[PDB]
Every structure is written in C-alpha cells, then in structure tokens.
Amino acid sequence: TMEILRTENIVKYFGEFKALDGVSISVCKGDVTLIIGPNGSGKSTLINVITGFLKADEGRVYFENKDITNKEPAELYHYGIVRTFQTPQPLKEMTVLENLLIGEINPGESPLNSLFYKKWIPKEEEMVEKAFKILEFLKLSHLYDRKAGELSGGQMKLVEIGRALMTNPKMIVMDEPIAGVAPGLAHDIFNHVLELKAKGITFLIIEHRLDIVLNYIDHLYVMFNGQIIAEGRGEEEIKNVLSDPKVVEIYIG
Ligand SMILES: Nc1ncnc2c1ncn2[C@@H]1O[C@H](COP(=O)(O)OP(=O)(O)O)[C@@H](O)[C@H]1O
Ligand code: MMC
Ligand SMILES: [Mg+2]
C-alpha cells in the first residue's frame, strides 16, 4: 500500500498573503489522488511547489522517502515527477507528433523550455516509434500530422498528457484537465487515467469540484484557504466528504 509522495507542512506567501499554511499530504503507489477546492485556496500553488516551480517557504516533500524539497523541475524528471502543461501558442503551430516529440527534447521540463532547445525537430528513429505507440494508445493515432492548433479541447488535453508521457513517469501531475469540459469528455480524460494507472503510473490531479468522476477517485483531499479541510480515500469517505456540510458551503456560489 506504501506511500510514494508526502509533504511535511508546506507553506507559501505572495507578498503578505500566506497562500498555504503547512499543507501535508499522502500521495501514493498507483493511487489517483485528487485535490479539489474553490479558486483561491491555493491548489495550483501546492503544485508549483511540489513540482519545484514555486519554492516552499517552509516545509518538505518526499518521493520514495527522499527530500526533493525545492529541487528543480528538471531535477525531479529523474526522480519520477512530471506535469501537464497547457500547449503554448507557438507550439500549436506544429503537428501532434512533434508536440509529443518535444516531450523529450527536455523531459519533465516546460513545453516552452523544451521546444526552445529545438533548432529542428528530433525525428530520430526511437522517438518516432515511441511517440506513435503513445499516439495509438491515447486514441490519437489519426492525428499524427494534424497541426496542434486544429485540435479540439478534448483532442488537445490528451496530446498534453502524451507529451507528459514522453518521459515514462512514475507520477503525472494534472491541473484541472476536465475542469470546464462536457460530462462526456470528463470520463474520456479519466478513461486513459485508469488506462495508465493499470500501467504503473500514479496521478496527482486537481479539479475545482468533484461531481462526475467520483467512481474513479482512489483518494480525496479537500482544500480551503491553503489548508486541508477534509479527506476521503474511498467512495463513502469521499461522498460524505463532498456532501459534507461545511464542504458543500464553500461551493455555494
Ligand atoms: N503570482 C502570484 N502572486 C500573488 N498571488 C498569487 C500568485 N499566484 C497565485 N496567487 C494567489 O494565491 C491564491 C490561491 O492560489 P492559486 O494557485 O490560484 O490556487 P487555486 O488553484 O485554488 O486557484 C489566490 O489568492 C491567488 O490569486
Ligand atoms: C500508504 Hg497510500
Ligand atoms: Mg489553481
């Protein structure tokens, strides 16, 4: 059942505003950990911290029982950490394949800082084969040469998860992939989520609320104002924890 990632009271500040007041989690192996909370509670901050993007003012982060606190995102790549980045504008001007090919130009690193080491896209024998394999898996076989701009929101998010796949991570980090989408697509993003969970990959997803994908969740952790206000790790634990009075109040609006 072992744990794979645990923080030790993560704190953060943005001027005078303490965006995180010692956040301690329990991400683990093969689990589909989802952190939800209204906007402002610091959900995308705990992430930039866990990924190294934003520094921990005071606290720790352990992966495989190791201190990775404050390590560079480019450092974490070799530990097993990777994050799903929204595809940039100059990036949406290149095909789906290449958009995953760059996922290796710089692994565990920003699509910006990855493609910025690209003089001419790496059409090496192994990278092509690996990509196209991943393009079939994600059911995005038929779009290998479609510009990424021509991709719907749905077709897009999976090419972004593929880009993050082009490293072969032990854990992937997603910040609101279904947040906003139609219910048909919610299951779609999450479909592959279980298609990769059964391949040995651990997820750290983050959504505003948890409505549609409750039957997937392996572990829930709610957040309000930089802290953890409730937690479930089972269907009834989570249902109760969502339909928990104070927990359904912060979502009245
Ligand atoms: N660069 C920043 N400078 C100052 N405040 C920030 C910055 N980034 C985020 N915040 C603030 O931190 C709070 C919540 O953090 P945020 O990452 O936005 O969490 P969430 O994902 O729940 O919206 C908000 O008040 C937000 O505007
Ligand atoms: C121990 Hg999850
Ligand atoms: Mg956020």
Image (cartoon, helix red, strand yellow):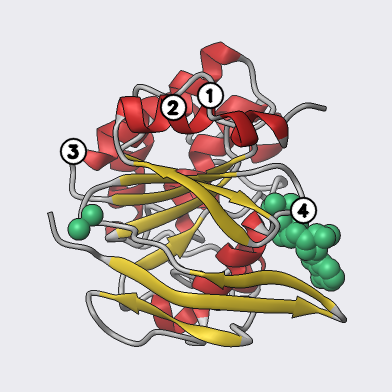
Mark 4, ligand 1, within 8 Å: the answer is: yes
In the picture of the structure, the residue carrying the numbered disc 3 is 198
Disc 3 crowd rating (10 Å Cα; few below 14, some 14-19, many 20+) is: few
Determine the secondary structure under disc 3.
loop
Quadrant of the drawing holding the N terminus = bottom left
Whichever of labels 3 and 2 marks the residue nearer the N terminus, that label is 3
Which residue, given by chain and number where applicable, does mark 1 sit on? 243
Q: CA distance from mark 3 to mark 2?
A: 27 Å
Separation of residues labelled 1 and 4 (CA atoms): 21 Å
Ranked by sequence position, the earlier of labels 3 and 1 is 3
Crowd around label 2: few <14 · some 14–19 · many ≥20 (10 Å): some
Q: Amino acid at mark 1?
A: Ser
Q: Identify the secondary structure beneath mark 1.
A: loop
Residue at label 4?
40
Position of residue 193 relative to residue 42, above or below, is above
The type of residue carrying mark 2 is Asn
- Residue extending farthest left: 1
